[PDB]
Image (cartoon, rainbow over all chains, first blue to last red):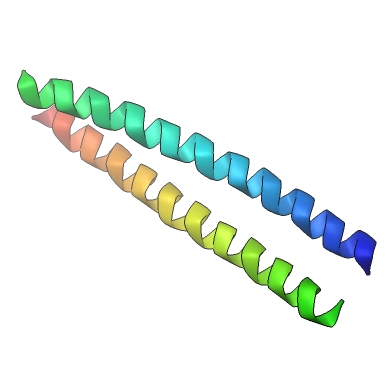
Length: 39
Length: 39
């Protein structure tokens, strides 16, 4: 059961990395949108 | 183990909730980027 919990934690870390990447993409696209709004 | 495995699974579910909400926001932002390209 401990091995299963560790695997779940590893998957949670992978999901955290994915969420961070999505937040970074959102921030970059929002910066592009802000420049577009200035234009 | 019964008190920790369920917590870890719920944490993974919340990570999936964040991933789903952020990816939905990213797709909606891509659609809004198509609209902004029309603009």
